[PDB]
Image 1 (cartoon, each protein chain N blue to C red):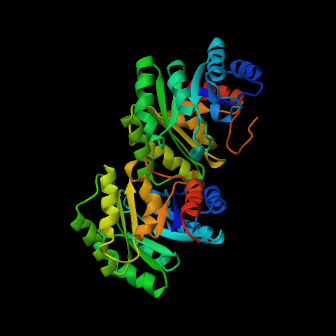
Image 2: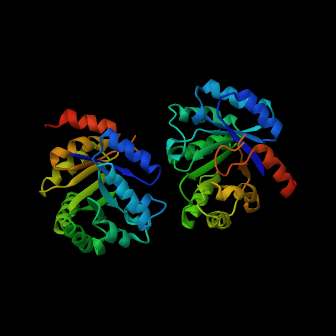
Image 3: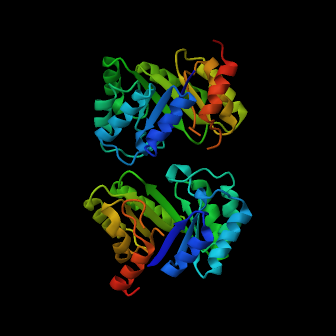
Length: 218
Length: 216
């Protein structure tokens, strides 16, 4: 699996350098956490990541799913999606799905279609619908939901197998930590790390690199 | 008119706070849009609205009218309709009308009997029949239909006058935007706003528009 680390624009150059040295394959630009969202500022950031040999995920999280409103969000996608290896758009932002799929497809890039639930792991039918809709819109479905028990972790992983295809599975919280490593066996293609952990369940980049080697020989 | 803001379970507490601070009168719980519809998860949300001093509309939209299947739908109405200020049930959910009226009436609450058409504004006889049936079942009839022209908006508003009584009238879509503000003069008692689709109006804007146009 590929290892990604989210980053805002603070001390960016040095954090990118650290992400590289520590083994990150991807840097996710959380533009919703940027103090500057001009098309050039973000473009240069994407280019700087590529300059270091890493891939990028262009994310501009909507406020309803843990992000913040970005006035020129749609413009950023139009202009930068063709330049980022991946673009993460929320399944809930229905009006941009077809549009971002066409843009990424034509540019030979990939679309991640995400769903986040910071409170609980939804019923199985919802898990399956999110996955099926993601594939229906031509993207890599991503599900990030808080586990309130170990059962919630097992359930998310097991139910995901009922909808075939590469996907991204994350059980957030202390209970779901194991999902960040074990997800691979269930078809999860990307795992997300912290550049030390600041929240329950996170795993530092350096540690995940060694775990990936120990369990999957990469 | 009163202003209602529909909300799903996403970032509920934060959204409710904004709704209260912006001036909403009602929060409509779109339970059909919830991830968890258990009696406790929903009851707690209902209590939260009341804790902020706002009224609630309990809605569990049927898949027939733009919602989705909710297995414990009946339990929710049975247990929560006596607590919610309003309960919205679809006229098409004929099997639950008498039951919901009895539950709400016994509890001193109000029943909204709704009709939704996301494609067009139906013929006048249908508009009148929906209003008549709503009243016949003891509820506040609600008609939410897509307007495909300004003519459709004027028509929905004018024909509704033929069946007197409190009601809720909404012409959805860009053309029907004006109905969200002007419906009140035609007897529409509640208007719906987004907290922050074509034709919707943000809560903050509607609160300002209401005071600008309506007499104290």
